[PDB]
Length: 203
Length: 203
Ligand SMILES: N[C@H](CCC(=O)N[C@@H](CS)C(=O)NCC(=O)O)C(=O)O
Ligand SMILES: N[C@H](CCC(=O)N[C@@H](CS)C(=O)NCC(=O)O)C(=O)O
Image (cartoon, rainbow over all chains, first blue to last red; front, side, top):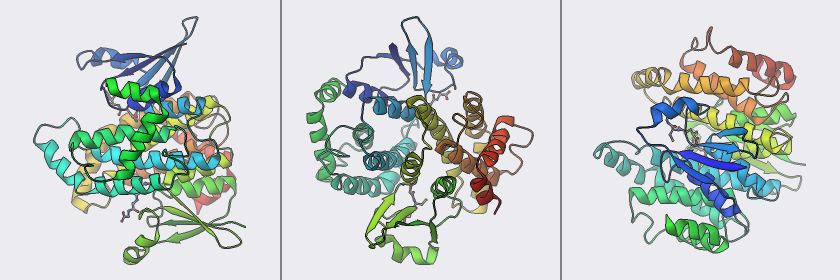
């Protein structure tokens, strides 16, 4: 099996797929599509949207996967990162749903001109962003372990890291002196996963 | 002796997926609808401060709280064999869910806005992402190994899809008239496959 991850942006929707693969110790090839090449490549991608995952086997047969968090969930599930009980599974999904709500605020700021981007940033950072970070903080407090859910790595952990990095892309100081539980989550995570720590250090 | 209470405000909102999976599973529950007037006082009693939420009471009267609509839905669906029976069916369940939620998110752009502003946004999405997403869902449905969204039996993907199509039609009751045969065909196949849901929806 050759796994290829096809995407536009370096820390976009593909991050959860890449992080999931990295934490599982599964090898993959990154293929980044330029803004210039997209018109040509679009019709070749089932569904016409990125990110997408092209899996090619030993005999050269191709299976396609699309919808970032559907792919992420599938891989996580295969590598035991979707919780170990129905109840852990619920808590993995709760946190993902929370992180995705936060991500959606961030998305409001994306590919807009330097001007409109900063009016939206100011609106969300005084709006749903702190509300959602508080909700995530409380969710983290309720874990039975040191990570988002239980004591071992799940998709919840990886989706959370990616969304937090997005918030700090909007205001680098936003979590400075605040949300100890979030800061602590990342500490505990990089310790449970040398791979991810190594992946994230590089970029 | 679990008492399941579904707490919400809309009525055909984010709770719908929870209600529909309970209905399909033939699991009984109580609807508690929160009025605008009552929300200020009820809000601090809901963990997370957001609806919908599910309050589960045993025969002793201990409380377990569930929040995040699609985390609750997924947990219920998983418990009742509606999240696919293989890892690949599971991926396909999530793919369709992800597609439906993209559509839902366009619909949300129109909500709780004054009549005039709502008409400007409705026109934008209906000539933009809405038809693009409906075409993607149509092709997803075509790729099913059976007559429903994934395989031949009910999954969460089926219920999330019908909820989102009803939202599209709330925006323009004619939008799918003579279009998207596979979507109409899906709902047909679904009501037939689930008397309980057909009953639930007719009323
Ligand atoms: N539900 C999303 C859909 C992906 C999506 O909205 N892709 C955008 C960029 S992140 C895209 O490929 N736009 C190019 C196009 O649609 O032509 C996912 O997580 O996979
Ligand atoms: N967590 C997401 C979203 C929850 C959400 O945005 N709920 C809103 C309305 S649909 C809410 O209860 N807001 C009340 C408030 O925040 O004061 C879900 O349950 O699907």
